[PDB]
Image 1: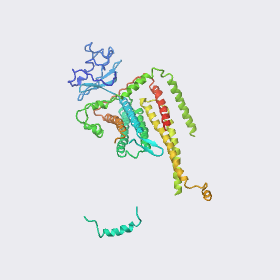
Image 2: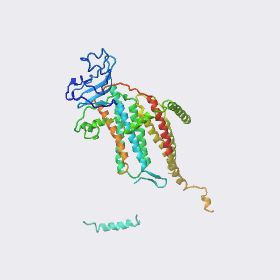
Image 3: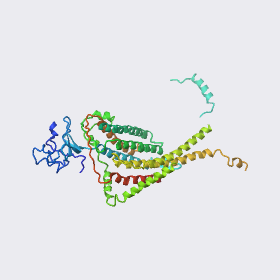
Image 4: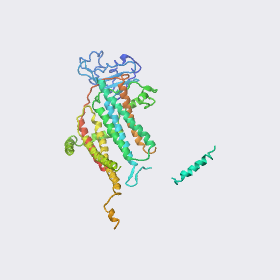
Length: 166
Length: 157
Length: 91
Length: 72
């Protein structure tokens, strides 16, 4: 029941790739994401309806943006006046099957919310191991004789007479 | 015009990434190498600064001088079974292999499972009285906070 | 010298004075209300709470630092005094 | 390292989403392979979205401040 993504398509227009394949892609089949009643009353009961969108306040889907090399992007929109298009969501295809393109700040908020919850849960476990005591503290759950100078000096005399030998 | 208005926010938003990596990559090595000599104020100060400056900077770059949070289009267009080296160039080796499902996985707009129960609670606390008593409570508490800041401003001199 | 140690103790005392006021000011400074201009306010309240949590712990650790730095001078004062030093020797 | 295990993965939880944000904002900035379109639509809130969030946010902020004060 969410606008942010469905993956139901029809197998009729999957293998065709052309510039007009997204132009005729408005209401080829029913779909749940394709809004019914006022938006979809132009297709499937009138013929040659593409010139009749403005005379009887029918709503067509967006065909202005179209790329040939990679894939097709179909949209859902609304219009109560001619020469005006305002959408609510974009539905891009990937290898045939559709998906919805979300917003920037919405996915930003839904990702930083999980980030804040993750940081809080990371901070939560740190109290479970450190144990404090006012005296013991914190814990987790798991020379020379001052004659060596002449000792070493005459030992140095021994090193220049018996050196280490390999 | 508008594209530069997006850019002036998103460039600093991804500049915050550099500070976050400089924190976490140092934390990763210092946790393994220096697990001992436990100093709870030392890590509490790091947690406090991470809570303070990063959470203020990403908020000030996402909530003001920014494109509207319902405006822009997040579009994935290219994906391949093999490894696309452009992403490992951008992400500096992060998110490897470049699978087919990892591009839908990138746009993980679905929240945690407990978010469903807190939304259930948000539908549950509306069964009792809401926005009628709590509204005047938060109004009186906003006036109380105004009184408190007046007390501080008259006690600061 | 001795005056350097006196100045160091004075500087850390003034830093202890400054830290407490800096902790109490930022708690109530962030509590002010501002109008939203393309904000998506769902993430700001938890941020304010999570920043309030560390600011109150800053006051707690400031009190702990006061407790420790008082005891730091406690052993400094105890070694050189004259309340009964010249008096209790002959008693 | 047998301790400090969940904190590490919970930090990667914030790492991954922020990396995805960085990658998408570095591919939005590049004009290639990206479609830029100003879609100015408004989502209607059923409730007073600043005020209904202020019903809980400042209350929980003050309550958690008092609780973490009384902790120490």
